[PDB]
Length: 412
Image (cartoon, rainbow, N blue to C red; front, side, top):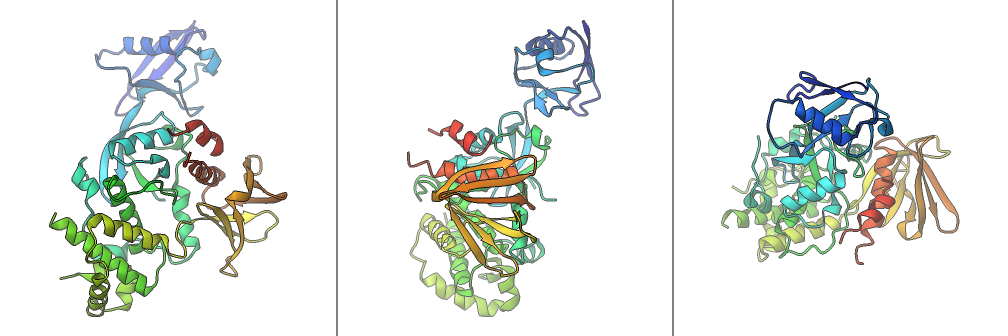
C-alpha cells in the first residue's frame, strides 16, 4: 500500500495534484475513480483518461494493474480529457477549430474528421504537423471554392525551386497507427488535412461536393505555390479554369496574377497574361462548376511529376544522397547528379517490405529475388513504410474499410 500522485490541472497540468493510496494490485479503473473522487467538481468524466509520460502511452486498459503496466511511484501520470481542440487547416487554406481524440490512432481521428466534413474515403487523406483568422463549420465554406489570393501572398510564401525542396513536405506526415499525444501534438496545435494518396476511388462530380472542392483546392495551391511544375500553356488553362470556377461560385478586372504561379507573374506583364487566359477560357466556358473542378483535377493528373511524393534517401552501398519517388503504383530512383530517373520498381512486383530498426533502413523484396535497401534522410522509415503499404492497401479497394489489413500493411 503505497503513494501515487497524479497531475490533475487543466490549464497548467502540473498546478493541481491528487494523491492516492494504491496497492500495485490497483486497477486503472479503480485509480481513475479515486482521482475523480478527490476532485471537488461535478461533470461528465467519461472522456477522461491517464497519460503516462515516460512510456508515451494512455492507460486505456481499465482492468490492468499498475504492476502489469509497470507503474511505480516515479511515473509521471496526467489525468485529462481524451478529446481536445485542434486547428485544422484545410486544403482550401481556411482553418477550422475542431475536437479531436488525442488517444485514438490517427487514421480513426482522420476518419472522424472526414465524417464531420462530409468527405468520403478518408483513407486517402491524412494529417501533417506544423512546419519547422479562424472559421466555423459550414457547408458553404467546405463546398464553395475560395477566392483567388492576393498575388503578393503567392510571391512571399516559401516555394520549392528544386526537386530536393519538394521532399520537405513529406517529413511532416503523422503516423496513422499512433495517436496525437504520442506524436508531440498538444491541444490548440495546427494540423493540416491533405490528400495523401493520389489514388481517388469513385470521385464523381455529383456525389462529393466537399471532397471535389477540397481536392481541387489542394491541386490549385500546389500549382500556385509551385509544388508541382507545368508549362506556360498548361498554366493558361489552369488559370482559365480557376477564373471560371470562381465566377460560377459568385453568382451562385480579371486580376491574372491571382491565377498563376509567381514564376509566370515575374516573367509576363498582366497585360500580356489576360488575353492568353481569356483565349484558354473560351475552351472551358460551357462547363459547370463541378465539371470545371474535375477538369482542373484531370489536367493536374496529366502533369509529368503528378502523383509522386519525393523522399531524400541513401541507397545501400551508395556514396551520395538520392531521391526516392513514391507514386501510386511504383517506386522510382532519381540520381541528383544526373537529374533523371535511373530505376523503377513496380508495386505489382513487390513481395515484402520491412524496416530493419537497428540500422534505420527500409528493405523491400521484389519478384525474381531483387532486393532494395535504403536509409531515410528526409522523412523517416515509418513515413516511407506507411506510404508504401498505404498505396498497396488502397489498391485493394475494388473488392467496409478493412482496418486490420491497413495496419498490417503499414506496419502498425
